[PDB]
Image (cartoon, rainbow, N blue to C red; front, side, top):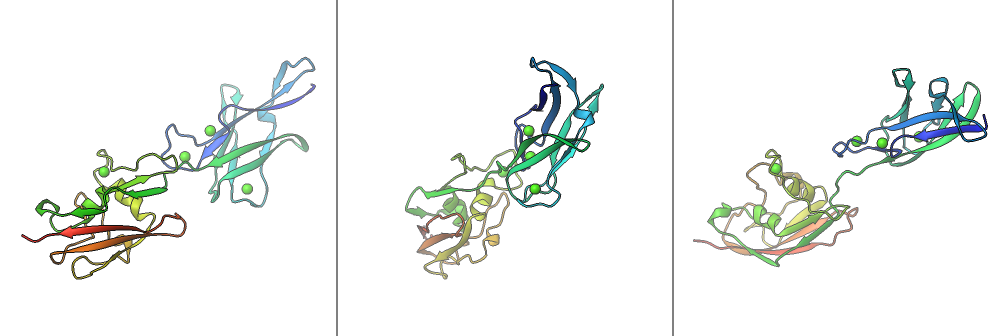
Length: 232
Ligand SMILES: [Ca+2]
Ligand SMILES: [Ca+2]
Ligand SMILES: [Ca+2]
Ligand SMILES: [Ca+2]
């Protein structure tokens, strides 16, 4: 044996997300022993022990377990409640002897709201709005993710609005210039999620400026949208 090879069968990454496709929930490891001429002379994946640090130091916590099928065992690395993303050094041992080291990576490709822009500067309401400006204010907004992809209410999920939920994930509050016409939203959880969208109820005929304030994490500047809600 010239040396040992730690083989990564997959992409070497573990997606911490809950809804990634295809499912990327493990790292697959094989350990070969090779001769001087580069030839595989043994699959010793079963005879080794794979461990990470005994005490967490980076918030990346994984689990190393064997998986034997038809005399063929693969070391499967799974997530064990990691709170951060990044590299985790795995140490491969034959009893007492360290053979090598491989880095697995925990990632999180979960869709976060990253960009929010307004289309028009003004919106008007009609009878079809049923006295609530939220449905039209939302339609006047464009939400993108980390990948710059549109965040949109999907019809195959009639329970909740993905676009409204994406806005509320980054919104700190909506200030009205006149609470008598439309009330200000201090608690964004009041922007309720149903097939019927509500939260910006019209209490009186009038024109008002709704200012959308976002959290410090998102770094998104305030957005001012004038809303006209005429009477009969
Ligand atoms: Ca996942
Ligand atoms: Ca993987
Ligand atoms: Ca760790
Ligand atoms: Ca839906």
